Amino acid sequence: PQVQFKLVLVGDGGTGKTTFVKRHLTGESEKKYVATLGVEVHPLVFHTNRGPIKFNVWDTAGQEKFGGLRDGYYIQAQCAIIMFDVTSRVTYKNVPNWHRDLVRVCENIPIVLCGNKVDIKDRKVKAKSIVFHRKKNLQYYDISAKSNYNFEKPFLWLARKLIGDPNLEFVAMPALAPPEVVMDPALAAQYEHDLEVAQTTALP
Amino acid sequence: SGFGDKFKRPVGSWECPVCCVSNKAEDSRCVSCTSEKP
Ligand SMILES: Nc1nc2c(ncn2[C@@H]2O[C@H](COP(=O)(O)OP(=O)(O)O)[C@@H](O)[C@H]2O)c(=O)[nH]1
Ligand SMILES: [Mg+2]
Ligand SMILES: [Zn+2]
């Protein structure tokens, strides 16, 4: 038997959930289609200092555009990612809804909040605005699916919570699709400096 | 120590061949996607 976790990947349509999970090349080529739910399960293997961990990532077929997701999608989820678009303020305002929809079925499973598309210059949702994770004591990460920026951070955090081992490390990065856009290393350092500053600012 | 050294599926459980969710022995269908216990 293998150590695998069902990871539900939720968020508004157009936030980049499918682009994100597709970065993991073997998860993409070995994804499984669930006809009854219209879902694709990407087996995302990660290799830790204590062995392989497989995140079976559930990705929608775009049904989130027309309403909430059915129970079956959430059932037995052991962890989750809530994604939003840093270029669409409205997607950030729906994070609480997705959070509620998720906890209504799965209770206090580990959750990571991800703001996608940080490779874009015209960033609308800045670090100072992102506060929901602090209210619910969740972990947040900037990411850019199309540049593989911080791709492994959410999965590393989840694995540590799920295993109960804060010293857990990925010994090697999974084979990822080549970056389709460049992520200015400085812009990444500036965004990372904006998060730590925002982390040391009071909640309004 | 490795997880696999101390990891074991609950007695009677079965992984769903369609969506990989782990189900109880008594369940004839998958509690997530409704597929049948193969
Ligand atoms: N610049 C940039 N564009 C992205 C990124 N991720 C997705 N896009 C685009 O956002 C649109 C929606 O992508 P998709 O993965 O289908 O979002 P989903 O509805 O949540 O599955 C598409 O046009 C993507 O090409 C990113 O990380 N950076
Ligand atoms: Mg999609
Ligand atoms: Zn199933």
Image: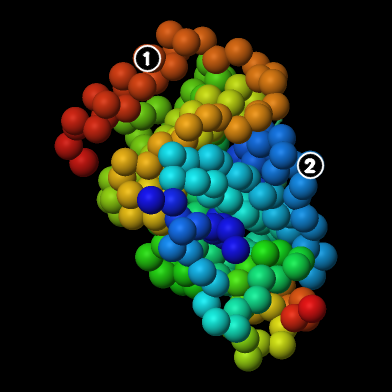
Residue to which mark 1 is pinned: A190
Counting residues from the N terminus, which is met first, the one under dot 1 or under dot 2?
A: 2
Q: Residue at x 47, y 10 (%)?
A: A185
Contact, mark 1 vs mark 2 (Cβ under 8 Å): no
Residues flagged by tags 1 and 2 on a common chain: yes
Determine crowd level at label 2: few under 14, some 14-19, many 20+ residues with C-alpha closer than 10 A: few
Location of residue A9 with respect to A145 vertically, above or below:
below
| Residue A3 x, y percent position in the rendering | 54, 57
Residue to which mark 2 is pinned: A29
Can you see residue A56?
Answer: yes
Q: Residue at x 72, y 83 (%)?
A: B29
The amino acid at mark 1 is: Gln
Which residue appears farthest toward the bottom when viewing the image? B26
Can you see residue A11?
Answer: no
Location of residue A58 with respect to A171 vertically, above or below:
below
Q: Secondary structure at mark 1?
A: helix
Q: Secondary structure at mark 2?
A: helix
Q: Residue at x 69, y 21 (%)?
A: A178
Determine crowd level at label 1: few under 14, some 14-19, many 20+ residues with C-alpha closer than 10 A: few
Which residue is at the front of the view, A180 or A84?
A180
